[PDB]
Length: 167
Ligand SMILES: CCC(CC)NC(=O)c1ccnc2[nH]c(O)nc12
Image 1 (cartoon, rainbow, N blue to C red):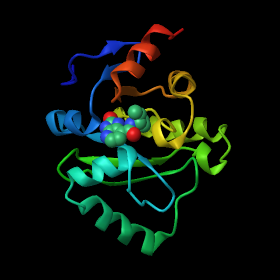
Image 2: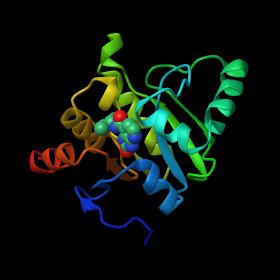
Image 3: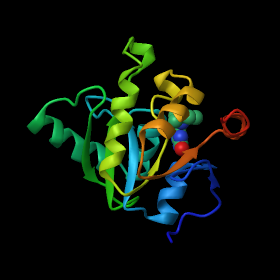
Image 4: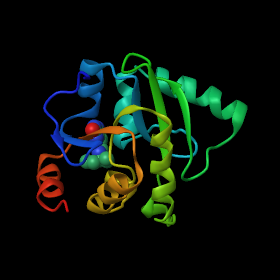
């Protein structure tokens, strides 16, 4: 038993809710919150911008030190950093950004990072401003992640569509 509340169960291991991931993280304090990162860990908008804002920019400060030491992530890759006031840890995962022309097949590789964590609160990778089809992203999630994932979908209209179209 865990503390996530109000989720619809999609599969054995995937759950979904119409929620603001920032508010969900602050209430749940999950072990892992996933950020929809880019390779530079520049948290300017979308989920990243909102998570970073909720940390009072501490996420960005930590991220800039990470990049200065290690260089950029790979598309499809990830790193574990602090969760600040939102979670124990933040798993920064880089899904392909369709608005940059990145290969959508890398979306499966991105979701594979979730398998290194038993339970995660996460957004749909490559959705929103990353330009992928969220229905496709949900399908890849379900077909790739084997650990327990709680998906927060900010847009109620999208949440209902994802549920109604789920196979
Ligand atoms: C998954 C990408 C997209 C789908 C609507 N979400 C956002 O761009 C976003 C922006 C700001 N705050 C948020 N909180 C949350 O859960 N998602 C967001």
